Amino acid sequence: ETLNGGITDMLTELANFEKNVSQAIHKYNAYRKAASVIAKYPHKIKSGAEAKKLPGVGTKIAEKIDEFLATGKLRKLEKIRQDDTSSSINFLTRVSGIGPSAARKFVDEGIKTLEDLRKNEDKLNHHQRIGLKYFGDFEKRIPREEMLQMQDIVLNEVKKVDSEYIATVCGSFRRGAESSGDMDVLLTHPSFTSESTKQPKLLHQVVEQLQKVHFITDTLSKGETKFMGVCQLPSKNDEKEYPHRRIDIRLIPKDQYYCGVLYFTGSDIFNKNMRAHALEKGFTINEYTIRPLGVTGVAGEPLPVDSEKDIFDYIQWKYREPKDRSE
DNA sequence: CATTAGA
DNA sequence: TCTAATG
Ligand code: NA
Ligand code: NA
């Protein structure tokens, strides 16, 4: 957590590279595991050799630790940090819709910057376009005060369309968070479950609504189960227009909401922990269900959930307000 | 780890 | 159909 810091940070840097700038999946996967084990270990790696002891810790990585250990640096890092081609990749990549693959491609054509990409709007697709045209606000954070803003509206049309809908803005907002990146609404309707072969309309109904009135302003992607998009709070009585904000609406068989709800809300650790616990408590929690463990090694059989509560009772735990679902 | 674009 | 990008 701190005795291995320099390591694990130098290494990840290392890994993050091969996977992007370069296509070296393997080497990339390697530094990660390495960065992984070297971080576990309880002592101060005083030398690569002592490190080398560890699994994944080959001659390659060890050498690296030695030079980082000896001098406050590492050239390969100092070189990469410098690399303008690389450097670029790293950045275009910020464009929602640009990934590593498209990064290299653009760069190899010569687009390496914001403007570069403007002049080549044609060279972008709808997604990457909106991504372009929204470059700034996509980076911008979202105040809770704003979360709480949009939340309101959303649940309004939701209810206005069909009173039988259920929506819940999940995430860290869900967990109290003084600010957030995007809105995660989980949605479900009783008239849709495990079997009841769809009703794409259910999802398609609401997107229309929100859109109608003004919330949704863009289409990033829409499928019969998950809609991807943009939104903007109405710009008041002027002098202040709200900026553009990512949004994700997703359908759900009412017979799997609670776990779905439990889960997305996290925290990544809270889940992991409560999840580890059900194992003892003779269970198995995972994204849409909770099944009873059968000694043979494994079992199945989805227990019935009506609330975040059933899940808790089942594993015989304390209902944890989302607020403190922190870990 | 799954759902969408798009080519 | 695959392959990229998101989450
Ligand atoms: Na070893
Ligand atoms: Na991106």
Image (cartoon, coloured by chain):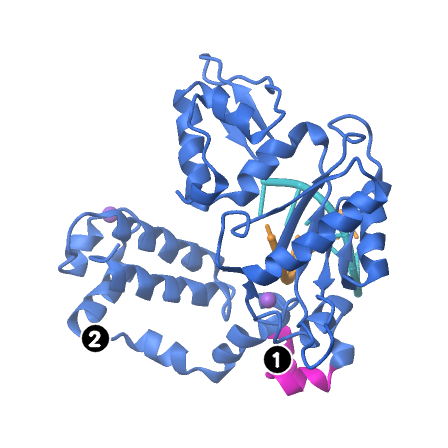
Chain colours: A blue, B cyan, C orange
Looking at the image, which residue is at 55% across and 23% down? Answer: A310
- Mark 1 lies on a secondary structure that is helix
Near-viewer residue (A242 or A58): A242
Looking at the image, which residue is at 43% across and 21% down? Answer: A316
Q: Which mark is residue A162?
A: none
> Nearer the viewer's eye, disc 1 or disc 2?
2
Callout 2: chain = A
Mark 1, residue position: A108
Residue A155 lies in magenta, yes or no? no
**Crowd around label 2: few <14 · some 14–19 · many ≥20 (10 Å):** few
Point out the quarter of the image occupied by ligand 2. bottom right
Q: How far across and down, in percent of the image, does residue A26 sit?
A: 45, 55
Q: Main secondary structure of the magenta part?
A: helix
Query: What residue type is disc 2 on?
Result: Gly
Q: Are marks 1 and 2 in contact (CB under 8 Å)?
A: no
Near-viewer residue (A127 or A100): A127
Q: Quadrant of residue A16?
A: bottom left
Q: How far across and down, in percent of the image, does residue A120 sit?
A: 73, 83
Q: Which residues are magenta?
A: A104-120
